[PDB]
Amino acid sequence: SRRTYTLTDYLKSTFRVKFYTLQWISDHEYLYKQENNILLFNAEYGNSSIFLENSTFDELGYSTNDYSVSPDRQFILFEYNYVKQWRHSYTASYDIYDLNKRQLITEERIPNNTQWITWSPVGHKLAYVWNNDIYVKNEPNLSSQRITWTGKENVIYNGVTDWVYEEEVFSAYSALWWSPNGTFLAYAQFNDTEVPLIEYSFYSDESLQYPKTVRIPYPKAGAENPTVKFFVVDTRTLSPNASVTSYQIVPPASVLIGDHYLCGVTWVTEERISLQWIRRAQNYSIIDICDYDESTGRWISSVARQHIEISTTGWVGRFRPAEPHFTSDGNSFYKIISNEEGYKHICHFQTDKSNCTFITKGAWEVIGIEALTSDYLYYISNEHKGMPGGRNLYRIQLNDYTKVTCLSCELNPERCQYYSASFSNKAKYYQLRCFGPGLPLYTLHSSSSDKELRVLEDNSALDKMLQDVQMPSKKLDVINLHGTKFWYQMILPPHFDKSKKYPLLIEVYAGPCSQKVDTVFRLSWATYLASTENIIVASFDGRGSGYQGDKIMHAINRRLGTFEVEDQIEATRQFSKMGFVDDKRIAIWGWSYGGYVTSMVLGAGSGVFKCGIAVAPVSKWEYYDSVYTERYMGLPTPEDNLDYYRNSTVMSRAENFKQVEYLLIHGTADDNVHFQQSAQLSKALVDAGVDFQTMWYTDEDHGIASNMAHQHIYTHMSHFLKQCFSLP
Amino acid sequence: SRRTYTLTDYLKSTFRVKFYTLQWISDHEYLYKQENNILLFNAEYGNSSIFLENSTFDELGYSTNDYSVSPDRQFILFEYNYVKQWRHSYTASYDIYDLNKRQLITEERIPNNTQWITWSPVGHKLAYVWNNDIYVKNEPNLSSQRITWTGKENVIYNGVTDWVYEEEVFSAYSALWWSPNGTFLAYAQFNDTEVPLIEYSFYSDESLQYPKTVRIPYPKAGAENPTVKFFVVDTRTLSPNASVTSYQIVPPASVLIGDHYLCGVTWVTEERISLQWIRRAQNYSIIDICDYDESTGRWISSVARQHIEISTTGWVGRFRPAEPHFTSDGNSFYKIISNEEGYKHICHFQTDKSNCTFITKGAWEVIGIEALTSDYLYYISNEHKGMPGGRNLYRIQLNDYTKVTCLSCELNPERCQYYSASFSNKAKYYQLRCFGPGLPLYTLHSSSSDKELRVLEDNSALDKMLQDVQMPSKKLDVINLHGTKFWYQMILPPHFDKSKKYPLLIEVYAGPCSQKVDTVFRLSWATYLASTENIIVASFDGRGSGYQGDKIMHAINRRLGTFEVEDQIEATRQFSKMGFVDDKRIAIWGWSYGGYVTSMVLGAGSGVFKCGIAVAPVSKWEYYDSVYTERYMGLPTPEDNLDYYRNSTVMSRAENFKQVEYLLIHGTADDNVHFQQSAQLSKALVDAGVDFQTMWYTDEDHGIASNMAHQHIYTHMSHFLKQCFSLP
Ligand SMILES: *[C@@H]1O[C@H](CO)[C@@H](O[C@@H]2O[C@H](CO)[C@@H](O[C@@H]3O[C@H](CO)[C@@H](O)[C@H](O)[C@@H]3O)[C@H](O)[C@H]2NC(C)=O)[C@H](O)[C@H]1NC(C)=O
Ligand SMILES: *[C@@H]1O[C@H](CO)[C@@H](O[C@@H]2O[C@H](CO)[C@@H](O)[C@H](O)[C@H]2NC(C)=O)[C@H](O)[C@H]1NC(C)=O
Ligand SMILES: *[C@@H]1O[C@H](CO)[C@@H](O[C@@H]2O[C@H](CO)[C@@H](O)[C@H](O)[C@H]2NC(C)=O)[C@H](O)[C@H]1NC(C)=O
Ligand SMILES: *[C@@H]1O[C@H](CO)[C@@H](O[C@@H]2O[C@H](CO)[C@@H](O)[C@H](O)[C@H]2NC(C)=O)[C@H](O)[C@H]1NC(C)=O
Ligand SMILES: *[C@@H]1O[C@H](CO)[C@@H](O)[C@H](O)[C@H]1NC(C)=O
Ligand SMILES: *[C@@H]1O[C@H](CO)[C@@H](O)[C@H](O)[C@H]1NC(C)=O
Ligand SMILES: *[C@@H]1O[C@H](CO)[C@@H](O)[C@H](O)[C@H]1NC(C)=O
Ligand SMILES: *[C@@H]1O[C@H](CO)[C@@H](O)[C@H](O)[C@H]1NC(C)=O
Ligand SMILES: *[C@@H]1O[C@H](CO)[C@@H](O)[C@H](O)[C@H]1NC(C)=O
Ligand SMILES: *[C@@H]1O[C@H](CO)[C@@H](O)[C@H](O)[C@H]1NC(C)=O
Ligand SMILES: *[C@@H]1O[C@H](CO)[C@@H](O)[C@H](O)[C@H]1NC(C)=O
Ligand SMILES: *[C@@H]1O[C@H](CO)[C@@H](O)[C@H](O)[C@H]1NC(C)=O
């Protein structure tokens, strides 16, 4: 050791962090890909048997990037020819392989350019989306039956989301939900007819003589939104000479009354489905539990089965309302909602009663419900040690809320404080995934006695490599702001010399319900900055941040660009007091919402920051999408919140940029935060006579994620920072 | 002490160079705007009188952008609501003011958004284009008569040029030509139905929620071109219930056979018109002189009145074939063409004979023919002192070509070496316009005696201001490359000390027929760089440059990006050996073709240049327009010149940029050299792992000309240069 973690190490991922991905297929069995082949591991004993030999991969077309085995284990889908679209959406080609006959299905194949495909929950039916229309295949070798005929590029989407539902509502491209036993196929249809189009140039390969213009129906704040229709198809009658039997379920009257969004769909039993709707304002949601009427095929709703959730001080949920988790019988459900104290906790609801009963409580929050059995409820929370940036698995007895045990807290306390879990079909077994503060660790456990069972991946290899590099140390702590304790973290350079003044880089996100301070282990750009360049990188979660109750999260309601920006400045000011920080060399950077906050901070005229870098920042809320923007800002009209939309633009702070060195970066093909945002920001700075630097990235999107652009952007930002900090 | 010429001096135009713009309206009178009053000057005796008092402008109620007086002096057109389109095109509102009854015409007004308007050459008829159609108004107070009905946005243009004809052929938006006595109105119709559209985003004011997509029919190299039709309208028959009497004149068969361009229109007499056409290849042009047949109304062509001009070593003319200058009777004409030695000289042609006689000859070139009488021909050439970068007015006796006199050469030999001239009707008087090397000097002269009559503007005001500043000096000289002498200029810092080593900035354009080395006086960014920052700024005209004969100019025929780039490197190499050049600090910069050459030089890997700045550069010829590109490069097909198109891209040299500091600048709304060119170049540099700097300019066009962007770009470039040269 006498070498550090370099920029090249980060960019080339020279130090590999291993993981362990598996797919549960029963209550005690899971599939795992080891050396290209799919093995069938038995959780209980660990006796692994080959389920699908490697080499059986004849590089069909390209390379199989994913597989899915039908529930009855008779077939397996091979996904290849992956073509990305937005954040979650993509199209791909699919091959169906018969596990019995061990033959490739060669007739009635899945179309090229398939948008979404899924096996039914039992058996082996298939439902897929192609050219915006839904198709169902009862048997892999049999021809598919067309379900919808209205699909139309950029207009009508059946079974898949449009741009805004994908990014802001579902966080998924799929909008198809098979019923438990495959009798019914539920789907949503999105109509973007009246949604304005964002248009931008895409240059493509150097050989393309004329650039292409990309057009996407994208509703900006206050614009016309897509409309949605939810249908339940009875697949029993699907036949070439038969029409489709379907029923449209509409939201309850209190939501149907105005613009709204469908935000959740949960099958309860084969004859009961739970739909969660939310008004466009997003401070009023309702769960509607509909029952199938065997005599008419209708799905009936009743006021007794409706559950309302509202927020008078903000929006419902973290990014959307939490999903209900029903009991096997469907007579009750558990769901995370805000406490009387503003903390998100699990409440128990009777399907036909309006009052619920909280089963957890405290100045901490449940992150999510992971599994439910007739006797226990497993959930993730940040209760342990009172640190909101930590995560642990817990089990609570359904007939005695006094009985709650933490399953992961003590397994490896110093190496593991941030966990996620994956349960087998009947919660009989669960994989624990520890992400930090130590090297990631994957383990298998049995719910019986919570026995450690075995280690799946401990990253021993990475550990060996790292003991030879001067790694920086990551510390978390708290600071007081306006009478409130907030968390921060600092990545400190190795062989830290307290007698020296180190330049400081604040990495910020700060969007509503964000969390930049946690105990997750990361080999990041910051690791390089601290290890090789001796720069301290700090992050702070202030007002508007999440997992600490609504009082803190809702503080920025209807006022984005205010308290979260001010808190970054105030916190940095506190950090600057430390004798080991060179207060004359403090920078700030961020991506997306973080680019916005970085810019707002730099335009605050605080005198605290010397320079900063904003990557793909929002610059004006009217330019961002309706769903996200309106959830936090209401509408941009004088009758509502136009005044706060107007004085929260970065452009309104243009003059103050004369005091700092600024680097504005943006991908020209960003379909999310449009290049427009940075183009308008640069124009305002030019108008104000302010000098600054820019870097556009041709054809890169919101992630500036291509291999060469990824390397180029961090290399460019690194040079900008060294220049700002007078570092050789 | 003494203040230097600062960046702010340049940016704010603190030092104002005055001029004297007049409009000849007869053989001895000219209008001149003075203190916003239009004055009428008599050259015969120097006396003047008020033509229009400025009180009139006060009464209009809008900012008058320009005015145009009818030839019979009874009316004046007032242009307002000016909205720029491309380099020459724009739209505007117009009022007609009756000078007799001194009242504004309020009836049958000219439509707003008018695209072009012009008085007839005699009287006061008006012809104008609105919504791509032509209208004629015999009287200011009378209703106009529509002439064409095919006008269609982005498809059919009547009376005005489409994008490429405006920029590359006519260097004007107008495509209408009244006959000498107003009998006929000729116009061209352009059809862009099959021309591909370039599309790019325009962001507009910050309040525009969604960007707009600008679309322009623009033929890039090898693409489908606009087609053209030429018509002569007989305006004597225009009447509300009369059809339009017109005749279409088609090109001669040697041009009609394939794609071609109309490149010139010259009215000879009321019954004779000269049309100049060129094949799409641009090395074959033909003049077709058509005569009006009074018995049928048609315009007749004859092989006897056709004159062919070709080029076997390159293209025809400098940027277009030179225009013919006809005698008053139309029986012969004078036109500049390349002679047997490859130098452009004046040839005398008989309208109905094929052979011509050269009246000028020598190792220098005639720039243009300025005026012609029955006895003399006046022209501008760079014959004096054999310096290609100088310009003087000569007069040649038509009956004895050996009798040639230089009218401007000895007027002010040290102050004035570069002149342009403007002759009155019948060439009785001329204004001489001296542009350098000293301060601009405008004088008036009598042709009968060649007496100087008077000084119109001598810039005494500016001269004074400049004595208190440390102005740099501009030196011109020659060097030998490959055995050919070429010219260069150096702008030298004040108190230039032969001993001291200075950083060097090469300012380059170097496109075909360019001339960056001349004796013109200029207050430029270079002036500031020399005066204040002590940087030597040099320019060099190498192979491909103009005004030095075809051997030099056509050297880069079919090979753009080769010799002109190599010559800039070689010249600079020689400069760095002059002892007063700090070879550790040599930079190069340019705009448009200059940005392309700057990039190619930086990508050459010569180790000569430390850094460079390309502004709105061409990066790949297939991205530029057909007319310009094909003129010098032919077609991008394997059958023609694809190979030289392929290895002349800036992207092909990306790897070599790792050795230099580069700044790429481009306006996002550049309709000429599309932003695409820099977007594809940056993408190739990113792919090659090259770090560099960028600066986009939102909504700026090829000129990056808005007041704020102009100040911003030079400020940004100065900082970059100073950082490259370690200048505080
Ligand atoms: C309308 O026209 C009248 C002329 O009848 C203009 O008046 C003239 O205005 C100019 C501009 O300021 C005056 O010139 C000045 O002369 C002094 C020389 O002592 C010089 O130092 C200044 O730089 C400038 O050149 C001129 O004396 C004056 N003439 C008269 C007759 O008063 C008037 O400006 C015009 N109005 C508008 C609003 O354009
Ligand atoms: C998608 O939504 C649009 C409305 O935005 C629907 O268009 C309407 O269709 C009805 C019936 O054909 C017409 O009477 C209206 O005039 C249409 N309105 C507009 C603005 O076009 C369209 O039918 C919907 N498509 C689907 C399949 O649901
Ligand atoms: C937009 O304007 C509001 C109202 O002027 C700003 O809120 C004030 O911020 C100051 C801090 O300078 C506080 O002292 C006041 O208490 C705030 N008043 C209100 C009504 O909350 C807000 O900060 C501005 N937003 C931005 C982005 O600058
Ligand atoms: C494109 O390739 C051609 C052919 O190789 C280049 O032309 C040669 O240029 C070199 C360097 O000046 C000379 O030594 C050869 O005599 C040239 N050969 C020919 C066939 O002309 C040309 O320079 C290249 N163009 C660019 C911009 O790199
Ligand atoms: C297939 O598995 C064997 C071990 O059973 C392994 O050695 C081989 O590399 C695998 N094939 C690959 C690399 O896909
Ligand atoms: C594991 O071994 C048991 C016998 O102990 C056998 O029945 C089972 O099928 C095996 N499963 C796997 C996946 O190896
Ligand atoms: C369905 O229609 C097709 C039409 O070609 C027919 O061949 C088939 O027999 C029909 N289904 C039955 C068997 O009723
Ligand atoms: C929800 O927000 C809207 C503003 O868009 C407001 O009119 C309404 O009163 C809010 N409702 C609640 C429950 O706060
Ligand atoms: C100049 O004087 C002549 C007479 O010598 C006269 O006709 C003419 O109109 C005058 N011009 C002006 C503008 O004063
Ligand atoms: C323009 O050209 C198109 C073919 O490119 C032709 O069909 C059309 O008739 C022409 N229009 C006119 C008005 O000449
Ligand atoms: C032209 O015809 C119209 C009738 O359509 C009539 O009003 C007008 O008087 C006519 N003008 C002429 C030139 O006779
Ligand atoms: C004009 O150019 C064409 C195509 O580039 C070529 O075939 C022809 O030889 C040229 N004509 C002359 C006289 O050079």
Image (cartoon, coloured by chain):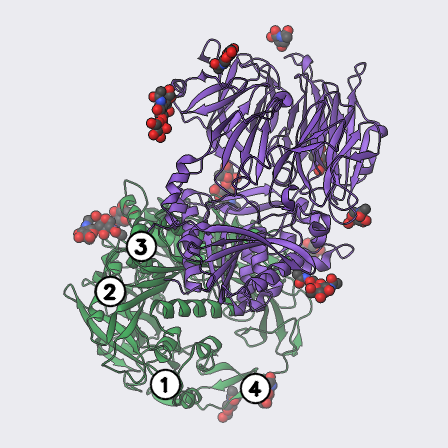
Chain colours: A green, B purple
Q: Which amino acid does label 3 sit on?
A: Lys
For numbered disc 4, what is the local secondary structure? strand
Task: Write down the residue under mark 3.
Answer: A658
Task: Write down the residue under mark 4.
Answer: A50
Q: Which of marks 2 and 1 is nearer the N terminus?
A: 1
Task: Write down the residue under mark 1.
Answer: A470
The reply to whether residue A386 is in sight is: yes
Q: Residues within 10 Å of mark 4 (few under 14, many from 20)?
A: some
The reply to whether residue B648 is in sight is: no
Q: Any mark on residue A542, and which?
A: 2
The reply, left or right, for residue B65 in relation to residue A638 is right
Q: Nearer the viewer, mark 4 or mark 3?
A: 3
Residue at the location (40% across, 57% down)?
B533
Tell me the CA gap for discs 4 and 3.
65 Å
Location of residue A423 with respect to A282 vertically, above or below: below
Cβ(mark 2) to ligand 3 < 8 Å?
A: no
Tell me the CA gap for discs 2 and 1.
31 Å
Q: Earlier in the sequence, mark 2 or mark 4?
A: 4
